[PDB]
Length: 140
Ligand SMILES: [Zn+2]
Image 1 (cartoon, rainbow, N blue to C red):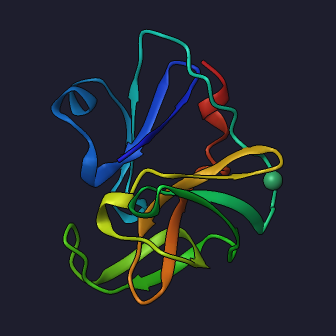
Image 2 (cartoon, helix red, strand yellow; image 1 turned 90 degrees about the vertical axis):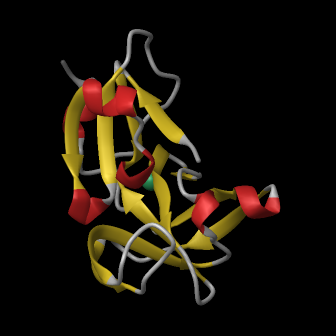
């Protein structure tokens, strides 16, 4: 579990969005596993605007933050998980590291701020849904 809070937006894994998220929907994209809902309070997080490929992510199934190198966001085949069938996920970054389903929502951060959230795992990789392209998270 976990979310990003920026401005009056909450960014969550689409597959973990609640009824309240859907009832306050701003934007969602199944291909990316992302959903954004509106908040009443202002968020604590800063979104990175960069092409960093090094950062640190939170792994809840280890109670640990790990430094990782990760690939640039791309269209990647993901094997079946507890929450999605095998499919192509867009805007996905991969790193070598531990990730189980419940690790979804852990933040990946670089020197500039939040890069994305854990979205995939298995076979010794962790996948992150990028958010650095979503410039609108900082306005309106
Ligand atoms: Zn960065």
